[PDB]
Image: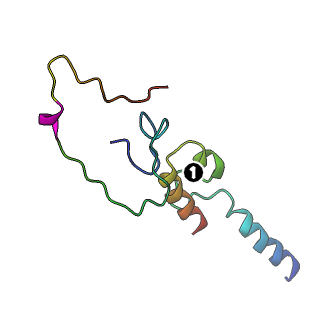
Amino acid sequence: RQIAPGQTGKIADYNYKLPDDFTGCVIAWNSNNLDSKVGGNYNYLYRLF
Amino acid sequence: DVVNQNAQALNTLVKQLSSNFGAISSVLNDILSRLDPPEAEVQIDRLIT
C-alpha cells in the first residue's frame, strides 16, 4: 500500500518508486510457505535510510 | 460606455482571480505544496477549467 503514483515511504523514497505515468499492473500474492523459518530467514535484506 | 465597460470587463477578470472553481481554495502553489500529486492534478484541473 505504498506502491502508488504520489505516495512516499519505505518503498517510494528509498529504492523503488513509480513514475507519474505508470502504464502497468499491480499483482501480489502470498508465498510464506517457501520463506518461513523458525529463527528467521535473514538472507533477504532491505533499505531503511 | 466604452472605456469603463472594458475596465469592468477587466475587473470581471479580476474577480476570476480568487475563485475556488470547485477546488479547495483559489491559492495555486500552496495546494501544489500541501497535497498529493494526483490530488493537485484534480485541483489544478478544476482551476484551469
The quadrant in which the N terminus of chain A is found is top left
Which residue is farthest bottom? B2
| Residue at the image position 23 percent from the left and 24 percent from the top | A41
| Residue at the image position 52 percent from the left and 58 percent from the top | B41
A34 and B12: which is toward the camera: A34
For mark 1, name the chain. B
Q: Main secondary structure of the magenta part?
A: helix
In this rendering, the answer to whether B37 lies above or below A13 is below
In this rendering, the answer to whether B8 lies above or below A32 is below
**Where, by quadrant of the figure, is residue B1 drawn?**
bottom right
- Which element is circle 1 on? loop
Colour style of the rendered protein structure = rainbow
| Residue at the image position 49 percent from the left and 54 percent from the top | A19
Residue A19 on the magenta span: no
Residue B5: give x, y in percent of width and height: 81, 78
B40 and B2: which is toward the camera: B40
**Where, by quadrant of the figure, is residue A26 drawn?**
bottom left
- Total marks placed: 1
Q: Which residue is mark 1?
A: B25
**Is residue B32 rendered to the left or right of residue A9?**
right
Residue A9: give x, y in percent of width and height: 44, 35
In this rendering, the answer to whether B36 lies above or below B48 is above
B30 and A46: which is toward the camera: A46
**Is residue A35 rendered to the left or right of residue B23?**
left
Residue A16: give x, y in percent of width and height: 44, 43
In this rendering, the answer to whether A43 lies above or below A19 is above
Residue A24: give x, y in percent of width and height: 37, 61
Which contiguous range is marked in magenta?
A31-35
How packed mark 1 is, by other alpha carbons closer than 10 Å (few <14, some 14-19, many 20 or more), is some
Amino acid type, mark 1 = Ser
A8 and A48: which is toward the camera: A48
Which residue is farthest left? A33
